[PDB]
Amino acid sequence: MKTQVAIIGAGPSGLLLGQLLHKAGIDNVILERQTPDYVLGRIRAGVLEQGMVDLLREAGVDRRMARDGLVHEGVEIAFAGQRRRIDLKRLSGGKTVTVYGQTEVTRDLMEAREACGATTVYQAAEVRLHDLQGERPYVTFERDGERLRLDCDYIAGCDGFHGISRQSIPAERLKVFERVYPFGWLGLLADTPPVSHELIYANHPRGFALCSQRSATRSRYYVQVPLTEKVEDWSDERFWTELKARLPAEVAEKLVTGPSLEKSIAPLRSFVVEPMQHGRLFLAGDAAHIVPPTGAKGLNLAASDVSTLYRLLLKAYREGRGELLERYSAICLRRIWKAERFSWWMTSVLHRFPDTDAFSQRIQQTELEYYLGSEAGLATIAENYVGLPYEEIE
Amino acid sequence: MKTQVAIIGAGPSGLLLGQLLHKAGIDNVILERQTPDYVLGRIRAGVLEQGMVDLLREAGVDRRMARDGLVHEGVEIAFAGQRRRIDLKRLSGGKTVTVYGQTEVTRDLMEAREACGATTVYQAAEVRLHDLQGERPYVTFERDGERLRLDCDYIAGCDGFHGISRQSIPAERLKVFERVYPFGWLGLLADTPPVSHELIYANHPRGFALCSQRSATRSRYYVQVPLTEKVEDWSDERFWTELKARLPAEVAEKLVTGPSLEKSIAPLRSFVVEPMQHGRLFLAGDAAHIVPPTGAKGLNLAASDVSTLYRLLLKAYREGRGELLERYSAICLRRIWKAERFSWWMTSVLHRFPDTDAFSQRIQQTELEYYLGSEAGLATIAENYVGLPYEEIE
Ligand SMILES: Cc1cc2nc3c(=O)[nH]c(=O)nc-3n(C[C@H](O)[C@H](O)[C@H](O)COP(=O)(O)OP(=O)(O)OC[C@H]3O[C@@H](n4cnc5c(N)ncnc54)[C@H](O)[C@@H]3O)c2cc1C
Ligand SMILES: Cc1cc2nc3c(=O)[nH]c(=O)nc-3n(C[C@H](O)[C@H](O)[C@H](O)COP(=O)(O)OP(=O)(O)OC[C@H]3O[C@@H](n4cnc5c(N)ncnc54)[C@H](O)[C@@H]3O)c2cc1C
């Protein structure tokens, strides 16, 4: 087969770019390993910064999110004493965030893609990339025994962390940087029970807790836990009792529990490859970098790069030129780092590491006091939470 | 002898409080171990935040510093690329800092104290504190064989890090917190040569460098160096060549060298005792806490506590009451920590630690980019550099 851009990866990155390109007139084919269920059972993110919203806007998840997603103007951060509110809008120069839900923005892209007639080879095992640095790359997947060959012009890796694009890049051509943090996150998606209205972030000595939403009668909760320590060991009841355990007056008559919408899980780290490019391969999303879940970045990360991948593709196709397309990893790496940074700070002011000496934790307490206190303090939080500015081009 | 407040320590803390108290009418006696030379050969600080200036103001080092001290409205921070200016006044809400010089503010207090007739027992060996928790404390020093006894009402420890007040506090009554950083600072006070006009802070990969002033034809330079690595090993010429080595276009035709005004030295760490109190003992300054030299805090630290020590003493003496004097370690510990914090951040964004993985240094670079870039970023720097607000009371 022949298409322009061949996408390995039907997660949201893969879909947006596909679902961006299509609208412009640059035929793409999504190449996905799994079934349209398994990707849809994947319950992750809830927070999308604007720009990834405007992006969705500049395509399609207008209808349903304009319709169904809580737009939020603040967060709260509690830290042994009390709850402290941020007011993102008046701190951020006037921006905010929407809690739509990852698995939803994903079902809409599979929705809208389905009706355009744009190609998507699901259950495609053995994907392989051939001819990267070449003038005509080609991708190869098995749909039987039936080894097929798709010649494209450009291959965009939206494979995710455990993808095959990244590895298919001559290692000496790459530069990794990564921190595997010592604790995972235990999620608990429950729906019957109503939430506590804004996001509550928490620095309790038993570890970190996080009350979140998906709907107005749908909750998303997490509590920091050590590694590989089994979930088969957690419980609804054992969850409800520990979450409760790390909160204030938000936690009792106020909180309502229930059995978990059979969603419960794990893990976190920071990782980044440099460069995000090879010949005609382009990594996007989790293929390229990994940021701790704590600053609601990652999907928001993948949107901002899927953005450059696409505008850079317009000019290639539509204008004449695009070696500008070499300047991609350049634009994207700027933002990935201020974002990686924002992510670790959050990670480390809120989390409880096995180590601290009364200085490190003395330091840890004081920085919260300072940032949650100073207006200059607070605006550094706000500014990064909603999203730093986006990007250059030309 | 009998006096009100007995001060162990003639450094600036000891002198200010003494030299504050006197003016109010609360007789004090300074008790110092060394000679008035050795304390005066002690060349340290150059930067004093306002408030410690206003304090000096509210006593005496008006004349000479109103006269001789460069008032500064900004600093510059360089970090492989270029120099970046801060503009403390327009970032700080309108404040600034004066580079007077520690050893000077010290000679003025010995100046002014000398003419009031206020007591100062120099060369007083064997100082010892007796009766802390008692209703009438007493201090004991040897001026011969001649063991003397000074009964006071209150003993204020302005002894410095290596003093005798702190140790004379029932250890289980105290709580220490400290970080011994892995590098010292090599100072080089030269005077014949003019400076480079504002302060230049530097993050160069060979370690940190610091160009500073004392006069308009007097310089103060430092370069980070590993520990106990001998100064007998440094040189003027070997200094001039390494400083130069960690700078930009500020460093050549621009910099002028010379032999060092025989001033060359070492070391740094963070340390804090909690509480800063015992019965009728009060620690002030380096006796109580130690902050890395890098955010020009320490003397500025000691001023802000010498301040509470003194106002708290007014009300005891002059009003009627002062159990308010129990609430001292309370006021002072607030500020010492936001200041300890500000000090480590500075220490760690500018210094080059033996460790960093391309993430820690990737993180290190990005945070500078972020703070030196963001306006909210910049104002968090400014606000802390000039001095956080001061304090409550009543
Ligand atoms: C607990 C948690 C909470 C988070 N919360 C937030 C939040 O609130 N806000 C926010 O903005 N971000 C959040 N994130 C980030 C978010 O998880 C991701 O950054 C986002 O899903 C990016 O996904 P992705 O496109 O790279 O790929 P993925 O979601 O991994 O999708 C990759 C796709 O590639 C396919 N694939 C894999 N290998 C192959 C192959 N060899 N061939 C073909 N196809 C293949 C997979 O089947 C999958 O469909 C959170 C993360 C976690 C873990
Ligand atoms: C390289 C460097 C640069 C610095 N730069 C700055 C800067 O730019 N700005 C800033 O604000 N701060 C700066 N600081 C901080 C500054 O050094 C101190 O915080 C400040 O001098 C506080 O001094 P202190 O009063 O506690 O005591 P000290 O200076 O130690 O004086 C203590 C006094 O007590 C006496 N004493 C000791 N033991 C006894 C005893 N048993 N009995 C009686 N007397 C005794 C000593 O003889 C001495 O006179 C810097 C520090 C360093 C190391």
Image (cartoon, coloured by chain):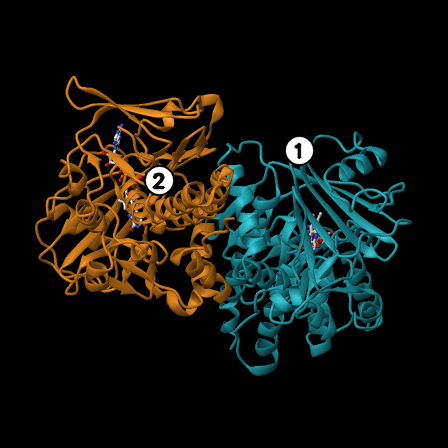
Chain colours: A orange, B cyan
Where ligand 1 lies, by image quadrant? top left
Q: Residue at x 68, y 68 (%)?
A: B50
| Residues packed near mark 1 inside 10 Å, few (<14), some (14 to 19) or many (20 plus) | some
Q: Chain of mark 2?
A: A
* Residue bearing mark 1: B227
How many numbered callouts? Answer: 2
Task: Label 1, secondary structure: give it.
Answer: loop
Horizontal side, residue B141 vs residue A279: left or right:
right
Q: Which quadrant: the N terminus of chain B? A: bottom right
Give the left or right position of residue B177, taking residue A111 as reference. right
Determine if residue B153 is in view: no
The residue nearer to you, when weighing B301 against A201, is A201
Expressed as whole percent of the image width and height from the top left, the position of residue B196 reads: 80, 52
Q: Residues within 10 Å of mark 2 (few under 14, many from 20)?
A: many
- Coordinates of residue B188 in the picture (x, y in percent): 80, 43
Q: CA distance from mark 2 to mark 1?
A: 44 Å
- Determine if the C-beta at disc 1 is less than 8 A from ligand 2: no
Specify the subunit that label 1 lies on: B
Q: Which residue is mark 2?
A: A285
Q: Residue A206 appears at what percent x and percent y?
A: 28, 48
**Is the CB of the residue bearing disc 2 within 8 angstroms of ligand 1?**
yes
Tag 2: amino acid? Gly
